[PDB]
């Protein structure tokens, strides 16, 4: 989507492999605030917004 | 410490930086005090094929 | 009413101890008052800050 009309997706009730995304390393920028890219798997999240 | 890396991986070779080249090849400890020096070597290193 | 001075000493000590216990909850600028939440969510340098 365009930046002004940015798309929001709620992702819930599932198991997410954040580590595989970080391992892929196809992304120029992977900045995490209040959290680290590693140890994301250990953490549980009430809801995820993409 | 002598090695050649891809220009994108230069950021990974730093203390407290996680990347594929940092994780499986060269790891820099956060504590050590040192100078990291990188310069472009496109002319000699790169070759056809 | 007679034992009020003794009660006042007990109340002052209890209030000071309660304040110390309550102080633990305070964020103190950090992401979370709990020490382990910080350890679980961040790597040691980031956690260290």
Image (cartoon, grey):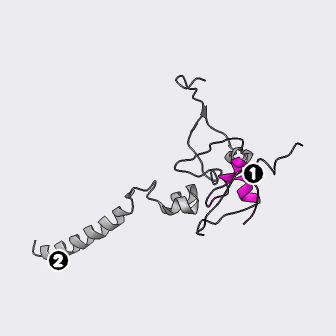
Q: Give the residue number, with chain letter if any, for mark 1.
A: B41
Left or right of B10: which side holds A9?
Answer: left
Q: Is residue C33 visible?
A: yes
Q: Magenta segment, which residues?
A: B1-24
Q: How many marks?
A: 2
Could you tell me residue C38's position as x and y percent? 52, 58
Disc 1 secondary structure class: loop
Circles 1 and 2, Cβ within 8 Å, touching? The answer is no
Residue drawn at x 53%, y 48% as measured from the top left? A33
Residue drawn at x 35%, y 66% as measured from the top left? C21
In the picture, the disc for residue A21 is none
Tag in front: 1 or 2: 1
Determine the chain carrying the residue at label 1.
B
Tell if the residue under mark 1 belongs to the same chain as the one under mark 2.
no
List the single residue furthest toward the front. Answer: B43
Mark 2, residues whose alpha carbon is within 10 Å: few (<14), some, or many (≥20)?
Answer: few
Q: Is residue C36 visible?
A: no
List the single residue furthest toward the right. Answer: B49
Residue drawn at x 56%, y 55% as measured from the top left? C41
């Amino acid at each position: 989507a365009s930046v002004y009309a940015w798309n929001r997706k709620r992702i819930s009730n599932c198991v997410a492999d954040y580590s595989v995304l970080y391992n892929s390393a196809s992304f120029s920028t992977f900045k995490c605030y209040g959290v680290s890219p590693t140890k994301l798997n250990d953490l549980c999240f009430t809801n995820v917004y993409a | 410490d002598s090695f050649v890396i891809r220009g994108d991986e230069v950021r990974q070779i730093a203390p407290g930086q996680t990347g594929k080249i940092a994780d499986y090849n060269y790891k820099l400890p956060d504590d050590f005090t040192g100078c990291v020096i990188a310069w472009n070597s496109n002319n000699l290193d790169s070759k056809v094929g | 009413s007679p034992l009020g001075k003794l009660q006042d000493v007990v109340n002052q000590n209890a209030q000071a101890l309660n304040t110390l216990v309550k102080q633990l909850s305070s964020n103190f600028g950090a992401i979370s008052s709990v020490l382990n939440d910080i350890l679980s969510r961040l790597d040691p340098p980031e956690a260290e800050v």
